[PDB]
Amino acid sequence: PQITLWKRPLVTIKIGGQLKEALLDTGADDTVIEEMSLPGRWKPKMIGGIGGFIKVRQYDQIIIEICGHKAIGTVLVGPTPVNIIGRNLLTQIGCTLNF
Amino acid sequence: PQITLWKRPLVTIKIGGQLKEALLDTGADDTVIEEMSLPGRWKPKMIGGIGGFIKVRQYDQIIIEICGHKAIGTVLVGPTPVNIIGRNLLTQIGCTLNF
Ligand SMILES: CC(C)(C)[C@@H]1Cc2cc(F)ccc2S(=O)(=O)N(C[C@@H](O)[C@H](Cc2ccccc2)NC(=O)O[C@H]2CCOC2)C1
Ligand SMILES: [Cl-]
Ligand SMILES: [Cl-]
Ligand SMILES: [Cl-]
């Protein structure tokens, strides 16, 4: 698809069998999801945003469907205001910026 | 152009007669630039993201040249860690997400 930016680029994602709404975010290096349960071990990570840093849990090799495209990669879980699909997964679905 | 997302989508912009590096950010509703002087009136605003909120100065009807494309709109100025080109100006240059 071609997504214009007059509205937030929100899409449906599927993770852990649950449908959620997430933002396709070219300004985010990483993918960060609101609190949920994910399988396996997690590692600590600090991520910096507009107002400073938040502590998140890093889960690797997580299966996530984004707007119907399958991705498998790192998902961070923490106190984010919105579910964010960052560049680590936008590259897996073949996303580019065009003008 | 077509910009891939293996690295941060950083571009040169010209604003208030100055050249700066900025991130093309589909996840940002607004354009936020590091501290600089801009002409005209401003009003205070709070913008939120990962890590909480920052106070910024809102300048309206500001011209920015982004990759050689001229665009006019609201520019927020404040203590952002990175210069961000948000949707308000990405739409003006005809930027879309494609996959
Ligand atoms: C959350 C929300 C509400 C959608 C925020 C929306 C938002 C809306 C605005 F009008 C103005 C600013 C911002 S924001 O700028 O706050 N932001 C945009 C986001 O792309 C950000 C850019 C950025 C800011 C500072 C440093 C580096 C990059 N990346 C980010 O937090 O990456 C983190 C997130 C995961 O990867 C690293 C997220
Ligand atoms: Cl990844
Ligand atoms: Cl605007
Ligand atoms: Cl359009």
Image: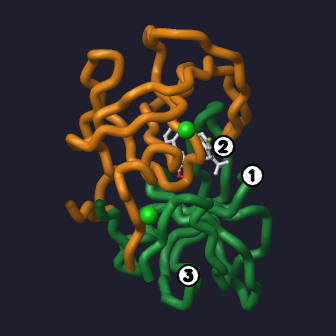
Chain colours: A green, B orange
Read off the chain for label 2.
Answer: B
Read off the chain for label 3.
Answer: A
Residue occupying image coordinates x 38% and y 80%: B99
| Residue A48 seen in the current view | yes
| Residue A6 location (% of width, % of height) | 56, 59
What's the amino acid at mark 3?
A: Ile
The verdict on label 1 being within 8 Å of ligand 1 is: yes
What's the amino acid at mark 2?
A: Ile
Mark sitting on residue B61 = none
What's the amino acid at mark 1?
A: Pro
The verdict on label 3 being within 8 Å of ligand 2 is: no
Q: Are marks 3 and 2 in contact (CB under 8 Å)?
A: no
For the N terminus of chain B, the quadrant is bottom left
The verdict on label 2 being within 8 Å of ligand 1 is: yes
Q: Are marks 2 and 1 in contact (CB under 8 Å)?
A: yes
Q: Mark 2 and mark 1: span between their CA atoms?
A: 7 Å
Residue occupying image coordinates x 49% and y 55%: B26
